Image 1 (cartoon, chains in turn blue, orange):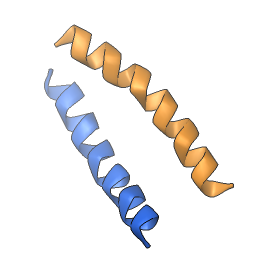
Image 2 (image 1 turned 90 degrees about the horizontal axis):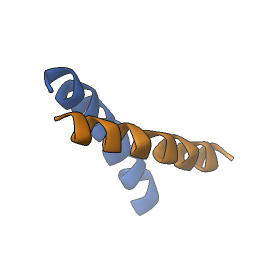
Image 3 (image 1 turned 90 degrees about the vertical axis):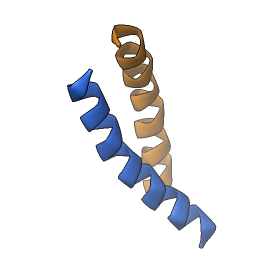
Image 4 (image 1 turned 135 degrees about the vertical axis):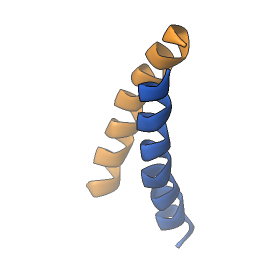
Amino acid sequence: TEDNASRLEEFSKEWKDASDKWNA
Amino acid sequence: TEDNASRLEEFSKEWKDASDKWNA
């Protein structure tokens, strides 16, 4: 559970960056 | 926890393909 949470929180920043790229 | 990890690892491949489309 902790590994899954950590890896997906890491992916969350990347996908937030992708969303920011989409906004521009 | 295992169901969540499995489903999000499945989503990870789809979002990696989405990032590949982002690059192209």
